[PDB]
Each structure stands twice: as structure tokens, then as C-alpha cells.
Length: 293
Ligand code: HEM
Ligand SMILES: [O]
Image 1 (cartoon, rainbow, N blue to C red):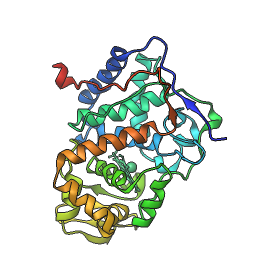
Image 2 (image 1 turned 90 degrees about the vertical axis):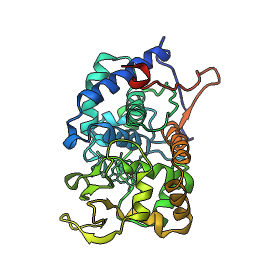
Image 3 (image 1 turned 30 degrees about the vertical axis):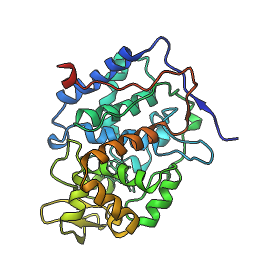
Image 4 (image 1 turned 45 degrees about the vertical axis):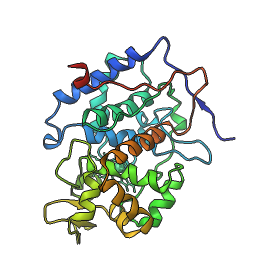
């Protein structure tokens, strides 16, 4: 008995309602740009979207973005989530202004907004995630380890029903933001353009000269002359033949990367949710820049 989480739109709420919430996060993203030495809050908002979705198990429909269990001490306090309470705190003023949206709709819309606002692809979003009880919070250990190889990555992602293409498109988001040693014991950005979404991660992986070096938290990571770093799991995408081909693909076609990332990131944030046929079509939100805001 895998669980059935069916979507329930928040009462009366339509598109205008969720576009208002998107503009609140976008306007706050402009205003609070100082964060993490001017990278701003976009990156960690994408990593919260991903970490609140990525607990899912396709075998039993436990985990995932449906029930917003990240708000419970257990998951909140997971070591793999070291750092995301910056993102949770960012979102708090917004949930108080719109007390009506559910936690998983807010945690997943937060990440859509961050990608779009950083000039990433339009990501279609569907509402209806419903907050479930403290007891439904999955246990710690479901999120990936950064110290492992291509085989680890493939097998890990099979649990969320992610194929290689989907994994490499998903990993392109590591063009964003940075690893911070106090959080994960890894230190460095992956590139120059930390807070605008591009295929820079692929170009860097193929063209930078990486060196395997150990960091002050005594973990190995791959380092470039230009001040960039790759995690062992990041680097494995060029070590494996099946992944290297798709990295070389996104490296040479920015629009293919945009398109696949949008599909794969929409799927990761929808895993586990049944949508009724009567449920509305996905929303596509205008950015502030398309709204002349
Ligand atoms: C093999 C799988 C993956 C591993 C092991 C992994 C691991 C990590 C690690 C170690 C960090 C640094 C966190 C910190 O020190 O603050 C990080 C950051 C980040 N990851 Fe992942 N990640 C993986 C896949 C993904 C995917 C699929 C996405 C989303 C589409 C994602 C998005 C991000 C983002 C946006 C950050 C930036 C955080 C910030 O600057 O605040 N990661 N990840
Ligand atoms: O991540």
C-alpha cells in the first residue's frame, strides 16, 4: 500500500493568486540581494525546492514535495539540509502574507521563481500539495552524498525515477551558488556566473583543468586555477561515458539544456502527486521583468 497523495487546490485559489505569491518572492529576491556575499537568495531557494522534493521513494510514495514535512524538526534538522534554513527564513515573511498557501506549494514555487528570476527556463508549476502530519516526515539519509562516483549517482537517482539525461540536466543547477565548508565540508563556486542560470557548469567541467586536492574539512574536491570547484559526484559526469555525452551536449546547446532542465525539474517537484483530471493546467508565471515590475 503505496500512499496516494492527490492534489487539492487551495480553496478559491487560481492563477492570479499564485502569480501574487511569485511576485512576492521575486520582489523579496531583488530586495535581499546582499546574501551570501552578493550571490543573493536564488541558489539556496533552488536547493530547498530540490531537497524538499528529493526525499521521495518511488517504491512506496513516501517523501517528496507533497506534504511539506521540511517544516518539522526531523527533516529540518537533517545534516544534508545544513544551510537551508536561510531559505526557509527567506520564505517566512511570504507565508505570513499569504497564510493560505501550503508548505510544499511554497517550498516548490520558491525554486521555480528563483530559476525564472535568474534568467533560467520557464518551469510549469501545478498547485495542490497538502501539508501532512509530523509523522509523515521521512527519515534522514535519503539525500545524496557528494563524495561518490557515477555508479552511485545513477543508482541514487533511479530511486526518484530519474534517468541519465534527467540526471545530467538536473545537475546543471550546480552552475548556481556555491558549496560552503561549514554546511557540507566542501568550499568554492562552480563558476563565475553564480546567480544567473546558464549551461556554464557543463562548459566549466569540460574546459577547466581540474586538480584533485583536499580541502580544510579534509575532503577531496576538484579545483580549477580560476578559483572554481567540482564535487566528486559532479566530476563523475565526465568520467562515465553515458554521462559525458550529455554534458558535451549541454555544453554546446544552451536551449536543449534549458528545455530538459525545465522538464526534469518540473518532474522532480511533482513526483508522488496524483492530479485529478478536473485539476487545472500547470501555471507559467511571468517574471517581474515581463510584468515591467
Ligand atoms: C549527486 C547529486 C547531488 C549532490 C551530491 C549534491 C550536493 C550538493 C552539495 C555538497 C552542495 C553544497 C551545499 C553547501 O555547502 O551549502 C550543493 C549545493 C547546491 N545544489 Fe546540489 N547536489 C546534487 C544534485 C543537485 C540537484 C539535482 C540540484 C537541483 C536541480 C542541486 C542544486 C544545488 C544548489 C542550487 C546548490 C547551491 C546552494 C547555495 O549556494 O546556497 N543539487 N549540492
Ligand atoms: O544540492
